[PDB]
Amino acid sequence: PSKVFIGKIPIMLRSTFCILNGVSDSELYDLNECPYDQGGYFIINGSE
Amino acid sequence: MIIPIRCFSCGKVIGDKWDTYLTLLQEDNTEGEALDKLGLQRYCCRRMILTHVDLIEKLLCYNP
């Protein structure tokens, strides 16, 4: 094939394919997050 | 964040009376009623240690 890049798609926090998903509470802090956040939002251009 | 210290209505100090409070409702099998053993006859302020949220253990773990 060719595996070529085609623009970029903004991910939604706490998803099946997010950077967190299966992360334990004790490890959410290390990352400066909050065990209460329930995702739902996008952080495009720096703002929710 | 941490007990208020000095109840809202009276002056009765409550900064002292928590390091000892929590060591009963989860460490002596006494009731919410146990605070009565801390000189809390008034409403009053005694709804101070009771209606409180320990928001610092869960805030302190953000180390710079």
Image (tube, rainbow, N blue to C red):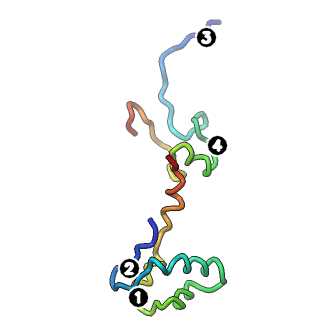
Toward the top, the furthest residue is A1
Give the mark nearest the N terminus, 2 or 1. Answer: 2
**In percent of the image, x 44 and y 80: which residue is there?**
B14
Question: Residue B11: percent from the left, percent from the top?
Answer: 35, 84
What residue does disc 3 label? A3
Residue at the spot of label 1: B43
Q: Of circles 2 and 1, which is in front?
A: 2
What's the residue type where badge 3 is placed? Lys
Q: Is residue A46 above or below residue B13?
A: above
Q: Residues within 10 Å of mark 1 (few under 14, many from 20)?
A: few
- Near mark 3 (Cα within 10 A), the count class, few <14, some 14-19 or many ≥20, is few
Q: Chain of mark 1?
A: B
Task: Check disc 1 and report its element: helix, strand or loop.
Answer: loop
Same subunit, labels 2 and 1: the answer reads yes
CA distance for labels 1 and 3: 71 Å
* Helix, strand or loop status at disc 4: loop
Instruction: Verify CB contact (< 8 Å) between mark 2 and mark 1.
Output: no
- Position of B59 relative to B49 (above/below): above
Residue under the image location 57 percent in, 35 percent down: A18
Mark 2 surroundings: few (<14), some (14-19) or many (≥20) residues within 10 A: some
Say which of marks 2 and 3 sits in front.
2
Q: Are marks 4 and 2 on the same chain?
A: no
Mark 4 — on which chain does it sit? A
Chain letter, disc 2 residue: B
Query: Which mark identifies residue A22?
Result: 4
> Where does residue A1 sit, x and y in percent of width and height?
65, 6
Label 4 amino acid? Gly
Q: Nearer the viewer, mark 3 or mark 4?
A: 4
Image quarter (top left, top right, bottom left or bottom right) of the C terminus of chain A: top left
Q: Position of residue B33 (x, y in %)?
A: 55, 88
